[PDB]
Amino acid sequence: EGMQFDRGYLSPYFINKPETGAVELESPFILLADKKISNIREMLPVLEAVAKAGKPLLIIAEDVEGEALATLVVNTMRGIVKVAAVKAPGFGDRRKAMLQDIATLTGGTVIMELEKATLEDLGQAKRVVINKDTTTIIDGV
């Protein structure tokens, strides 16, 4: 078991374990962004980095929307990208506080400019399970 908050996948097309309707990510990297992501040009640096490392990425942001989400989803559907996205839990100051808690458990840093983030700022966990209503981070670094 591990940490679990009540936020599910941003797109049902992130699912890779349909028999359970879940997204299971083994040894993923974790991005904690206290902002709404909409431009893909913004995340390219981090997407390039985790791709060289050959590990999946979990994006936990205030919201991931529009073009960014569209690209993430479509590329996942083709298999060119191994990523999943969910909204950050809580509201107001509680959101920020909870974001740091997740950062601490995984060893990451809550984003500084998103364009200049690295694997060093990313969190890590042994496994992550995401369904329609929740996200469970298992064994954080």
Image (cartoon, rainbow, N blue to C red):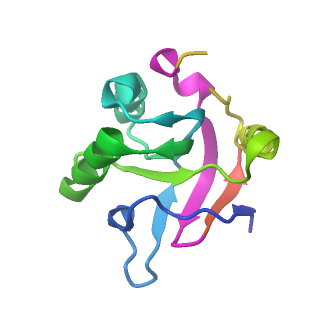
Judged left or right of residue 1, residue 80 is left
Residue at (71% x, 55% y) in the render: 139
Q: In the rendered image of this protein, does residue 32 appear above or below residue 21?
A: above
Estimate the x, y position of residue 131 in percent, counting from the top left. Answer: 52, 71
Membership of 129 in magenta stretch = yes
Foreground of the two, 12 or 54: 12
Residue at (54% x, 16% y) in the render: 113
Estimate the x, y position of residue 70 in percent, counting from the top left. Answer: 28, 48
Estimate the x, y position of residue 111 in percent, counting from the top left. Answer: 62, 26
Is residue 79 visible in the rendered image? The answer is yes
Is residue 105 visible in the rendered image? The answer is no
Foreground of the two, 10 or 48: 10
Which quadrant of the figure has residue 120?
top right
Residue most toward the front? 92
* Magenta stretch in the rendered image: 114-133
Residue most toward the bottom? 19
Residue at (46% x, 82% y) in the render: 20
Q: In the rendered image of this protein, does residue 75 appear above or below residue 31?
A: below
Judged left or right of residue 28, residue 74 is left
